[PDB]
Image (cartoon, coloured by chain):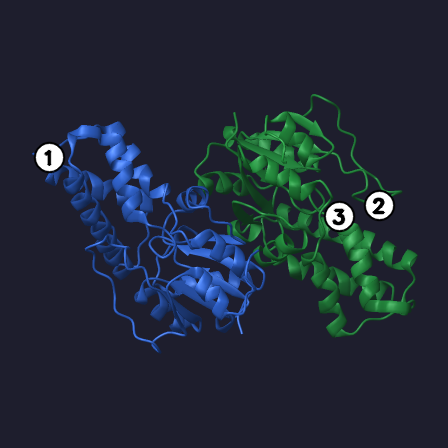
Chain colours: A green, B blue
Amino acid sequence: QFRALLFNVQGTLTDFRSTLIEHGLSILGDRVDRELWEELVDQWRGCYRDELDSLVKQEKWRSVRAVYRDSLINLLAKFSDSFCATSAEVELLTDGWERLRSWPDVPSGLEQLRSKYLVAALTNADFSAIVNVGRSAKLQWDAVLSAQLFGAYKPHRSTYEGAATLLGIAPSEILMVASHAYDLEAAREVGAGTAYVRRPLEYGPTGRTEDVPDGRFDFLVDSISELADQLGCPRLG
Amino acid sequence: QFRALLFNVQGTLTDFRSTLIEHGLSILGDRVDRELWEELVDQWRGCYRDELDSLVKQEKWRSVRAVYRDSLINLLAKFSDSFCATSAEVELLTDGWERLRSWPDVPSGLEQLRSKYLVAALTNADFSAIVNVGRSAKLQWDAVLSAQLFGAYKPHRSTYEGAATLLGIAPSEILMVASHAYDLEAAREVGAGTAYVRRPLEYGPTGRTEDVPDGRFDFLVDSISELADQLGCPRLG
């Protein structure tokens, strides 16, 4: 049925929240309490989503590192009574989004899939960021694709179409994998299969995750290894 | 000194001549003698180089699969008194360029390099072809880049520049690796370091390879593992 799996990376494969919480506390030290920094990180992810939503509607693209940097500067101003950061620290903090750690199932899940399928990233992050995340999150791909290559963010149909034509594969032979329904719904409109990965801690222990019923998408799993099993991939030794 | 190594793939890392000789003999069987098919393969590689040279001068890009297909059709006509192929076999034969095998040093050499450096392909082959070659040649990369992404073939400066800006790395911190001097000279003009890999069998046992003296490029090696040693990469177990 499928020749390749195409992955949403941030959140789907990476625990960005834990990464940015620990990264920020490492840089800022005793000047901020953990509970306060956690709140900023949650608003930071929200600002990122709000900006990409706005740029998608305007059919525009800009550097996602810049999106993260600009939203951090705005949030630092909002939190300025509580703590401060230097310009140098703004850059170091923004780097956290290029140091994401993976969920524990992900490296072995990707390896298991590759016995039968090509695996590729299709991320909204800049190309340089996802290459760096491959090292921090221990991701090995057949190909790395970024919104930067297409001048458009997911869910714009040109991202999925361009991924298909670059890979030389029909959309019906691509399985889109994500912990976000918006991405799967958009891939399905281009012709791709859909696999939803539940990430109940993506927004934290007291966080808010989507509710996806069985049957909405082609697969509904709790880990990448489970998806590999359901696709008939033999287990690793 | 360097953050990433950027690789010429066909020839530099892959024995395309042996691949296409055995691939063609597998498809065509007893209808062609090995010595005759070898001659076609050598002319086929030459036709590919002649066409890319022509397209570079015209500042044009087209599918490299189409370049290989069109040149094969021309050569089949030239050799038509000796043997024939069907349209279906033209496609199967053209597929050989996406099934290239690596030189024996290459998979472990790339793995050794990755302890210290990002490694990426920068190939003139289409994106889909180099993804397929990663499986046949056992190549694992941090990123895959193709002339198709830039609408221009190497040696056009926009390929090296675009690779640098996509990776987020200064050209002076990129080491270009190739068994072809034209590619290294062009990368050097953009600011990259240069590593020449001798491949004395690239054009066959009685084949013609360049003569490169010590000092022309930053490194001059006989294998990727040797390059890794010279870059201070610890050996594999």
Q: Residue at x 33, y 50 (%)?
A: B15
Answer few, some or many: residues within 10 Å of disc 3's Cα (few below 14, many 20 plus, some between 14 and 19).
many
Residue B62 in the figure: left or right of residue A54: left
- Give amino acid for label 1: Ser
Same subunit, labels 3 and 1: the answer reads no
Mark 2, secondary structure of its residue = loop
Is residue B98 visible in the rendered image? The answer is yes
Image location of residue B8, percent across then percent down: 39, 58
Q: Residue at x 18, y 44 (%)?
A: B40
Q: Which residue is mark 1?
A: B80
Is residue B150 visible in the rendered image? The answer is no
Determine whether A189 is above or below B56 in the image.
Answer: above
- Give amino acid for label 2: Gly
Q: Give the alpha-carbon distance from disc 3 to disc 1, as whole Å.
A: 60 Å
Q: Do residues under tags 3 and 1 come within 8 Å of each other at their CB atoms? A: no
Q: Residue at x 42, y 55 (%)?
A: B105
Q: Which mark is residue A204?
A: 2
Mark 3, secondary structure of its residue = loop
- Residue A19 occupies which quadrant of the picture? bottom right
Image location of residue B91, percent across then percent down: 29, 33
Mark 1, secondary structure of its residue = loop
Quarter of the C terminus of chain A within the rendering: top right
Q: Residue at x 70, y 63 (%)?
A: A95
Q: Which residue is mark 3?
A: A15
| Mark 2 or mark 3, earlier in chain | 3
